[PDB]
Image (tube, rainbow over all chains, first blue to last red; front, top):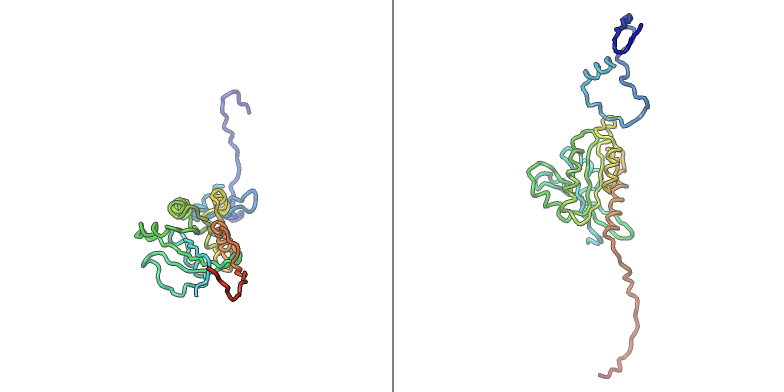
Length: 56
Length: 194
């Protein structure tokens, strides 16, 4: 490809899907870089936690 | 008789439902009468310890928060020398006005008090509304004794409350020396001349 000084060029990358019966996407969510910490209440609804896990 | 030496009064203060009374009634020996909370408001139980070969009565007054006793409880902090703000780690809105209780109790209690800060209900360890390190820090720049105060199978109170009576004891244990009374002589037959 070539991009000169402002000219955008939308790359069209083909991939496949993922299979929901092959990966579990409800596993421990947003894993911390370091184990431990305060362990405070999440303060969010369980359903919200589901969509935050999927969107990560 | 009575035969104790000093008598301190120590308020327990906090929001309602933070768990002060169940914390009290394990911990003091008893108060001999169950009585009731909310007829005059604040109830009170005694505890006797001894420090430095002096015998101490400490009178714990735990205070309810039903919004009716507005002028009444502020009259009950008059002369109060020992204090304990209790907060629970499960719920979170009590900590928003723990500082409110602290600045109301620095007002009109004594010239100088010794306020402890205690986290009730550590048994439900998997529900921490506020981190313990933040409350530990907030105790550190407010000159306050801090204890975990875990609920059930705990002594956190049986060492921290004794340490509170120690720190409030040398705030008022001023000085004394002796009462020996051994100086006897002068058993004569009195050849007086006036």
